[PDB]
Image 1 (tube, each protein chain N blue to C red):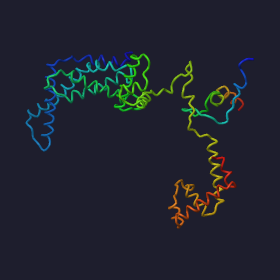
Image 2 (cartoon, helix red, strand yellow):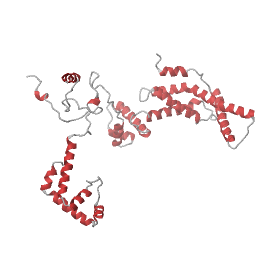
Image 3 (cartoon, rainbow over the protein chains, first blue to last red):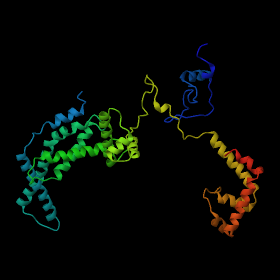
Image 4 (cartoon, one colour):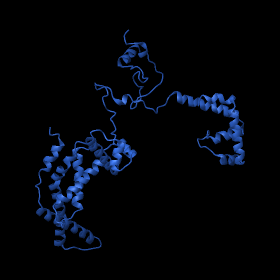
Length: 49
Length: 305
């Protein structure tokens, strides 16, 4: 049984903490944070239109 | 390159030849004569004299010669400023700023000065230059400005704690330092708390240079989203419930708790704008409060608290 259990991985956020200098949502499961909607995903949804 | 302005300055100040007590006496006499000359020229300028040409011309010569001598002595002792300032680097301010502040202290030392006491310039100036460098390093060093009395007691605490750390081997306790400095332990703790250096939000908390502290600081003052909407809903529900009250009752409540302008009116004002006595206002107040305590219009607003 490997140490990659689901309870350590599942995560969700509707509204939580916010970063300080920039006002983005924070990062990581220790906080709530969101998932980085990075550059490549921006390309993907530009490609869909 | 020669980008080191330290060098660009030292090679500059190594020019003017170094002087002696003999030339110092001559220079100081010239400076004082010039300052006196300009003082008298200002005095005789006002309501005064159509001066003789030779007299006026050469007293202006003295006035300018005094400044020449002053600047000459300043250039002479720039090197002394450097020699005294080198020892206060490695911490706080930078070398160049220290040299400039020490120069200011030197202007003060040559200004507020005497030569009839018969002393080499450095003896007296050294004191001033050291004082000026220390004054600057105290005020314009720490980001949050802490004043000089507090700075000196901070330094005394630091020295005592450090020396007694080595003496004891173990770190001194707050009562040991409080007894040593003849101050109170809470003051020891306060000073220690004031020695804390504001960390930089610019630091690679991760090994590679991509993770900065400023990107992990929850701002515990932001709009909670649900809190704001909840407050709006509370406003609405409370407004409705108060509208259940009678006109006198609604008015007394709104004015008593400032729901109409944000100004909390008190009993005398409310009785004045309604033209009754404040006891009547307080009775209507108590009656209304008791009515609202009734579960019918109460349980609706309980959750907001």
